[PDB]
Image (tube, coloured by chain):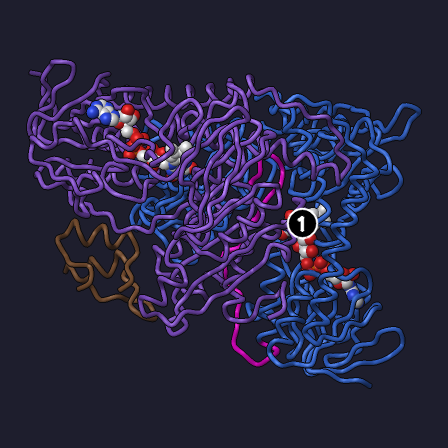
Chain colours: A brown, B blue, C purple
Amino acid sequence: MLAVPAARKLARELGIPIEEVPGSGPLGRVRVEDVRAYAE
Amino acid sequence: MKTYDLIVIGTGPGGYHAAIRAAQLGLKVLAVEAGEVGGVCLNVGCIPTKALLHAAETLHHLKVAEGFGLKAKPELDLKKLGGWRDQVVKKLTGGVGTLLKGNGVELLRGFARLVGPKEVEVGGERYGAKSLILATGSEPLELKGFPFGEDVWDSTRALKVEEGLPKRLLVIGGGAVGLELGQVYRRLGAEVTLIEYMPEILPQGDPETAALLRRALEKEGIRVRTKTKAVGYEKKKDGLHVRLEPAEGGEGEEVVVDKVLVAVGRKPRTEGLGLEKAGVKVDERGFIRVNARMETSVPGVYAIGDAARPPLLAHKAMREGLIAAENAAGKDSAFDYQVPSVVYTSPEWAGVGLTEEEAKRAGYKVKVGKFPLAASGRALTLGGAEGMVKVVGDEETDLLLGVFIVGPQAGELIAEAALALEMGATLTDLALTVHPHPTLSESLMEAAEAFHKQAIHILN
Amino acid sequence: MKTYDLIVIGTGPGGYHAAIRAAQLGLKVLAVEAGEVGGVCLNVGCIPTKALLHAAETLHHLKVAEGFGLKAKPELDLKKLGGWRDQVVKKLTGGVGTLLKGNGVELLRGFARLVGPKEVEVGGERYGAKSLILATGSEPLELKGFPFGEDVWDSTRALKVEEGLPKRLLVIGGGAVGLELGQVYRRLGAEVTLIEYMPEILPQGDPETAALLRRALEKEGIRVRTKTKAVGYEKKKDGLHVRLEPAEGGEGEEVVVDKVLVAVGRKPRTEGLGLEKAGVKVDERGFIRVNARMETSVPGVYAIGDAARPPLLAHKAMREGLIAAENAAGKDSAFDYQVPSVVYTSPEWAGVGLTEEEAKRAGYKVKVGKFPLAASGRALTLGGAEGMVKVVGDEETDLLLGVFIVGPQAGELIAEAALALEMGATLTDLALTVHPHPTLSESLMEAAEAFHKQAIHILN
Ligand SMILES: Cc1cc2nc3c(=O)[nH]c(=O)nc-3n(C[C@H](O)[C@H](O)[C@H](O)COP(=O)(O)OP(=O)(O)OC[C@H]3O[C@@H](n4cnc5c(N)ncnc54)[C@H](O)[C@@H]3O)c2cc1C
Ligand SMILES: Cc1cc2nc3c(=O)[nH]c(=O)nc-3n(C[C@H](O)[C@H](O)[C@H](O)COP(=O)(O)OP(=O)(O)OC[C@H]3O[C@@H](n4cnc5c(N)ncnc54)[C@H](O)[C@@H]3O)c2cc1C
């Protein structure tokens, strides 16, 4: 799993396991948007 | 008529990159060079200029060095410095020759004229190829009232510091070239005045960091006149009496210098090439028109670097050369990258991305973070810190938009900013990256933190 | 009893970052410091060592500078040097003090002792708070057979070059401390011999780039004895006769020096802290046990920096302070970052991420890209082009795994690598980033290109 720091930071503050957030790049890079997208 | 897969006109940064990348892709390549291998950058631009700056900086730092017990009575031999500068150029230009040969590229010496889309003439002989890449570079832009001559130098002549340092120098142009050469001359002992027509030097870059560079240059005795233009001059017994006036016009002042350096720009070398008759479209200023694929108006003919479009930077020409070659080789490449710009003065200046103004005009909700070098432990261990890092971003998406730096090693620190932009990093990503301490690079991290009002080494 | 929302023990990089970040989050903070504010890094570590290195480099470069005409008769006054060094330290520690006060943090001078998970004793007074952050740092590790004394120095004593330079020095330890102080002494005129027990210096880093640093150090006259260990010595009329043996043992050997610097590691200052009373657990090495949130075994009590766990680096301690403060503030932060490490010798060494060995062992199909500084234009304009950049990546995914650099400014260029790793960059992203030309940072871009066998300035 590859998640930029901003996303890992936000995932925690939301109580969301980062490894559970689906990415978006050509191959899974998790962005802040994705973490929020999963949050909703 | 010898034929090839590709013919490249010019072996400058853009040219030898296109030629070598093309070779790596399996194409039979012919490279034509009318002058010195390596182009402007290696011969009369980047390289010799950076070399002179390093020597000047080594000499200059000895003053501050006295502060930590380093006593010395430095004596710089200009003839020797010129020799070294030449030795450096010879190594690098010779290296390119070796490099071209090692990739199976054919190097042809001589001026090339474009006979047609797939044909070119050199020294009488004709040569053909399915693809042509135009990389002819640029040359010093002349200034009205200050024609180049014995007392009016272009950057090339200004590089030969061994042929006579003038007591007083007037530098026209507040861009990278003018600032760098002006500082070299000042540090070598000449009095230097630099004028710039726009409100601030480095008109295209961030005004705040550019102002810090100007004030730093003035502390060294370099007289920087912004919003000023040189109208004309008259040679007299005691020197060149130059008339200056405010940019918008007005009461002028007169100064006397021994030599004038004109560095107000560059002119693309696209004349007498046949581009006209060959259907290759050139714009108002002589730049070859091209799309993101570096393709001209004529299928199979590409243009790159300084001859193709601004900014006139070496790394930009190098990348365009790669893009051009790759498309000639049949791939599908396009130029869509952040291009940084650096000024190798001391302190150095570097920028990449959007300025606050460009960002706002772009519709982003602009927010900025600043960190001064005076708060950098590393900067202090280096003898003193004057400078700052400014990050520009969108406060709603937290997306980084631009980074501007003034201080030692700015040119080295901007690459991280460039990578950041390419990777779509947010200010938080930049702030959360653990930078090594103590390093100048920490200023970028702290600037990102200042953006969120939580910098640690300065009060927010 | 005075109470606060948080009590931080120690004001080194970790302590003051925690104290300040906590204050920014609205907490009432008390910071306790038993010695000098700023801790090891600012007083007897990072900063003073870097200052000495810079003075030494400035001096040493003058030799090379003769190549471009700079003639000087340099004399380095060691008393003045020591003075400047003290000035830098005082300026920075005063800075931390001003910062703590400006943030509303109360500074109490004294030695703190835990009396409970929410109370501390200082000089006899009682201070309590909901959360406690332990940032007590570390101290020089003593080597069997070489107890510290007038002739056996720790890093702190080694810093005081104004107290007289020994004619011959023996450095024990090939880590960052020994390499740096050893090169400083060599550059100031002392004969130097450094001994490392392991097969290569910087055993935790890339042996390829480490070997390049060792070789550059030997070229300056520093005798580097790897796979060797100092067993002991005896003081005689002509100096210290130290016994050396192979790492595993065997044929003894003798070397005579005037002074010995022991730099084999550090010991965490966790004793007499009243820990073994509040319930806070420590491991066998003496480090306070913590999780990724920097929480110890006692809720509300946190530990950071050198006292918590290796690596014993400043930037690491700083970030951990931020994590601890944010958590004391009721947030949810955790440490999961790439930690780079730098050696400020000349050439500098820097690394971040996985070495080839660690990556292969973890199961990645490893591929490496390399770029030598002998091929760097910028390195030439700076004089000697000694060094290289090596990138380690996954051949299957093109993902960057590690970066190692040896050369000038290695420490500044490693931040870009760290950011690359944090962002999940591939070798292609590194290569697609347009680096300024000419700059040392370009070596990283070309190393990425070499990994794909398409570098331009060297043959693939
Ligand atoms: C003083 C100075 C300092 C500079 N410093 C920097 C710096 O620090 N960083 C930076 O990024 N940029 C710098 N630049 C700009 C940089 O030099 C240019 O951006 C770069 O050289 C452009 O590369 P190019 O390959 O397009 O063209 P050029 O390097 O100009 O090369 C074109 C080549 O084509 C040859 N040629 C031209 N016409 C023909 C023809 N008809 N037939 C055959 N051969 C031909 C020329 O002789 C030449 O060798 C500087 C420029 C100057 C003048
Ligand atoms: C010679 C040398 C050079 C180094 N160079 C570098 C470098 O270039 N880069 C790098 O990253 N790292 C470097 N380091 C390591 C770096 O200095 C440490 O990693 C860093 O200082 C650790 O910060 P800290 O906050 O954990 O602890 P420390 O800085 O040790 O600070 C702990 C503080 O707590 C105080 N304290 C301790 N116990 C108590 C108590 N009971 N009550 C009150 N106060 C107390 C101490 O007096 C001290 O000020 C170097 C170390 C040395 C020795």
Residue B135, horizontal then vertical, whole percent? 70, 65
Residue type at tag 1: Leu
Quarter residue C47 falls in: top left
Camera-nearest residue between C297 and C27: C297
* Residue farthest right in this picture: B237
Give SS at disc 1.
Answer: helix
User: In the rendered structure, does residue B420 fall within the stretch colored magenta?
Assistant: no
Q: Main secondary structure of the magenta part?
A: loop
Please tell me whether residue C334 is drawn above or below residue C258 in the rendered image: below
Residue B38, horizontal then vertical, whole percent? 73, 60
User: What residue would you read off at disc 1?
Assistant: C380
Compared across the picture, whether C293 is left or right of C429 comes to left
* Residue farthest top in this picture: C124
Quadrant of picture, ligand 1: bottom right
What span is colored magenta in the figure?
Answer: B327-349
Residue B386, horizontal then vertical, whole percent? 52, 28
Quarter residue C41 falls in: top left
Quadrant the N terminus of chain C occupies: top left
Camera-nearest residue between C419 and C252: C252
Q: Chain of mark 1?
A: C
Compared across the picture, whether C89 is left or right of B183 comes to left
Q: Residue at 78% across / 50% down in the picture?
A: B87
Camera-nearest residue between C307 and C201: C201
Residue B250, horizontal then vertical, whole percent? 70, 27
* Residue C353 in view, yes or no: yes
Quarter residue C64 falls in: top right
Q: Total number of numbered labels?
A: 1
Q: Residue at 27% across / 32% down in the picture?
A: C137
Q: Is mark 1 within 8 Å of ligand 1?
A: no
Q: Residue at 69% across / 43% down in the picture?
A: B177
